[PDB]
Each structure stands twice: as structure tokens, then as C-alpha cells.
Image (cartoon, rainbow over all chains, first blue to last red):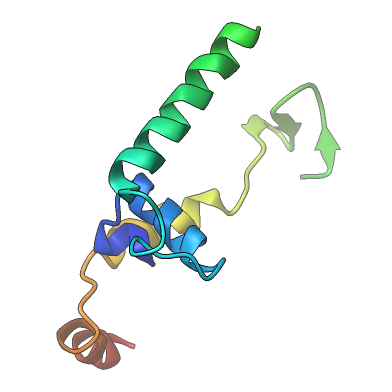
Length: 49
Length: 48
């Protein structure tokens, strides 16, 4: 549904986060928090192998 | 498929491949690219 609209991955993450009752007005800047939290995790995940 | 034979392959009279519904998603995904709640909802309503 959102793919057709063109929601970027970090936005879809915000949507999942909104499901927690937490929005971008609750979160630290969400674009930076989400982008770096996930990218750092992915880095660590690859190195973990 | 009935006579499954080796990974990804199935025999009838020919060495056919095994299929799944993923093909229908690529269809729906690229068929309905528009996504406006008003315009597309109604444009699609006509299609539906």
C-alpha cells in the first residue's frame, strides 16, 4: 500500500514506531535517529559474521 | 506439480519448473502504481 505511495524505508519505520504511541514529536529527530540506528546495526550485523 | 524431481524441477513430459504466487504480486504491484485516496480511489473504482 505504502510502496505504491512511495514511503521510504525510514518512513515505514516511523509508521511502525507510531504504532507504539511514539511520534516524531516524541522521538529525537527521527530522520537521524532512525537512519543511524539502523545503519549502525546493519554494519554490526555484517561484521558479526 | 506431481512428479517433483530435483530442486526447482518437475516432470510432466517436459522438465518444467516449480511455481508460486509471487508472480501475481509483481502484477498487482506494477499494475496499481497510482495511490491518491480521492482520484485513484475513484479511478480504480471504475476499474474494479
